[PDB]
Image (cartoon, coloured by chain):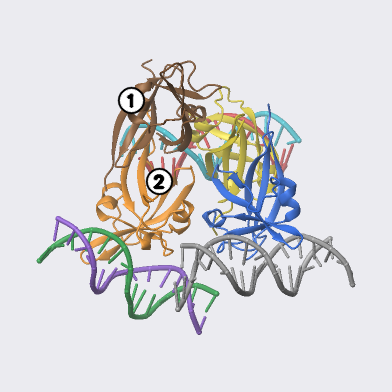
Chain colours: A blue, B yellow, C brown, D orange, E red, F cyan, G purple, H green
Amino acid sequence: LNLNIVPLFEKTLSASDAGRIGRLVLPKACAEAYFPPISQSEGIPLKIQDVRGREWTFQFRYWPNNNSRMYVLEGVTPCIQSMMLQAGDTVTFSRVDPGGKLIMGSRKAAN
Amino acid sequence: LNLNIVPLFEKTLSASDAGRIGRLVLPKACAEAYFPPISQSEGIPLKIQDVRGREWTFQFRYWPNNNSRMYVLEGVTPCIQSMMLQAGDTVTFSRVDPGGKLIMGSRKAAN
Amino acid sequence: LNLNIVPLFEKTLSASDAGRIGRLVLPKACAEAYFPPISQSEGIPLKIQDVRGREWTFQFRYWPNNNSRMYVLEGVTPCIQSMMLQAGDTVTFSRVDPGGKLIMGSRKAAN
Amino acid sequence: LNLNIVPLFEKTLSASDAGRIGRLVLPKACAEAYFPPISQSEGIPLKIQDVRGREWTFQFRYWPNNNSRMYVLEGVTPCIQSMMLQAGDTVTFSRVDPGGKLIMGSRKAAN
DNA sequence: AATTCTGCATGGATT
DNA sequence: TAATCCATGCAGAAT
DNA sequence: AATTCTGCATGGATT
DNA sequence: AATCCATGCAGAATT
DNA sequence: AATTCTGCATGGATT
DNA sequence: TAATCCATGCAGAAT
């Protein structure tokens, strides 16, 4: 056995995503591409560690938006600014295979 | 099957660690607590991935010093340069189980 | 407020303890005297600090094994090795008061 | 090489401690009992490891207050936020030997 | 030549 | 004091 | 044109 | 009547 | 009353 | 233009 980290996708935080309300809008291509598929209104909870083993629990959810859905991680506020990261910076999602483990990272703006 | 990340230790890079000399000094308590034990001064190769998939292979090695040992990773220059680390930034090592895979991260210095 | 460590109990590591499977077999008297009570043998996740300050989360669990049980901590091998313990060395458990925080420690064998 | 944690003391975080001023009042009894002695208002830098192995540097310092002193750690807001603590939670300090290193941990309020 | 690379030595800071 | 640790110095070996 | 920083000062709250 | 600490607060320093 | 949170629905952006 | 996406606004809800 030998494991490998695979990057899945990335999101740069909007002002809305960052803090306050507590939800992060996931790019919908990426959300269904790499995260679990859900049809249920309020979808599954997701559990994801960072590189230091710090576990986080979000609710992975949709909103019907017109014809199609809008994807969110709810319950993000501790993670964002327990990792002390504000708006316009980027949060990253990767995966450990085999086993499909979700791990997240975070890069601050280029300047 | 469920996988789990545990933090191992951190090192804040000295000018020699980030220097062109291409070596990183590991604290001896941390090297023996968390990296595989080594008998021969000629070390062992260690492979370490970051969040973004970029794997590195360093030589984990020691030097006789007084009577005790001094521990180093050699071959970090590709890694330093690539994640763009300077002296005073911090490199962190944590580990994935089962499989004892080594993963690294980094935070930039506060100023 | 001022804090106090109370020693609870010791185990001499068996050849089966830690190792590839990574479980530490607890004497049933000590698990029920000192660890939180558990009804289902799935157990609970338990958090324990080692003599290095490091916190770990192991699974506190049993197997029924006829009427009586056999109790284990799972996920101990990185921690045991961190303390440089080998079979025949000793694993120790202590309590911090107030608060009953559990500490996992170690003294190596008489030779 | 005998490893051993010694617990030193605890403090319950006030709204000013958990606040964003970033100074933590050490009770003068504990501050003089366990931290290195300081003669002069201008403090010394102090390094404290957290339970997950990350190093933090605060300023250990005092203020004249009536005839006696009032002691503080400055620069705690990122660290306090890191442990997801708020007013009424508890911060604890221990001393890992060999090396006399300070460890800071924390348990959240009873609810 | 003169520079870089290797392996250990040494010394400032801390326990 | 006495001891330890680790950032860096600095002598050969090698470009 | 604030906010944050400082260096305390004051006062509520325990004995 | 003491003492200790959570917080007020009034200038200085920094947007 | 009056701020917080839920679940959308609107409309600028970016294919 | 065409269709979505996604940043955010904003009413019934709920504290």
Residue in front for this viewpoint, B66 or B84 = B84
Q: Which residue is mark 1?
A: C9
Residue in front for this viewpoint, B79 or A90 = A90
Q: Nearer the viewer, mark 2 or mark 1?
A: 1
Q: Residue at x 73, y 51 (%)?
A: A30
Snapshot quadrant of residue C27: top left
Label 2 SS: strand
Q: Are marks 2 and 1 in contact (CB under 8 Å)?
A: no
The image shows residue C74 at horizontal and vertical percentages of 50, 28
**Callout 2, which amino acid?**
Gly
Q: Residue at x 50, y 23 (%)?
A: C18
**Callout 1, which amino acid?**
Phe
Q: From the viewer's perspective, is residue D65 above or below residue B9?
A: below
Quick check: can you spot residue C91? Answer: yes
Q: Which residue is mark 2?
A: D105
Residue in front for this viewpoint, A107 or B79 = A107
Label 1 SS: strand
Snapshot quadrant of residue C93: top left
The image shows residue G10 at horizontal and vertical percentages of 24, 74
